[PDB]
Image (cartoon, rainbow, N blue to C red; front, top):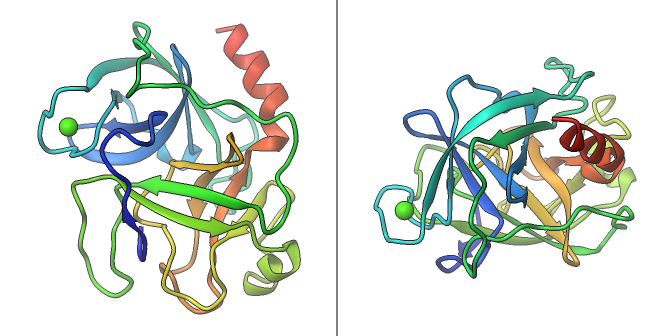
Length: 223
Ligand SMILES: [Ca+2]
């Protein structure tokens, strides 16, 4: 996350780190057995780590649970990152408490200028490299479709939205594919892509999870 602040430990309860030896993607816990992340984050041998703040020290509220199954969306296109969403099932169920919790799916799509919360462990610099060990947050608005599609001519589909500032310097990207964008209580997105990090007129782009609730709920009940 470039240009945000330290969330505070265990303040984003539904936040997950996917670990293949090292932190490589974020995700959201949606019930005790399932995680949603981005498809461009598929890896074999995923361990899911819940209740993290500092992903490098065991501070006492973590649960570490192996993934049993990953399900990338049927129509994910890794060239355009259309349909960038993936379901990850836990080998044993999480135990839900104050610091590990689910986040609700959408009944409806968020609209533009709704304030959202975007979290992750992502790169914090726009030029160069610095990764933080603790959870980071940014508060930003869902930008209008126009101002989204204008920054990426011919790249934005119905299944993405943009959030952040047109002006540049607050953004994630790097700084955590796969992580949550939560608005008015409900998971409305997944960090997908974005040219550079926090350039002027290069907002972050996010999977529009509202379009996928029917599939998430069907898939998760059959597996
Ligand atoms: Ca930890």
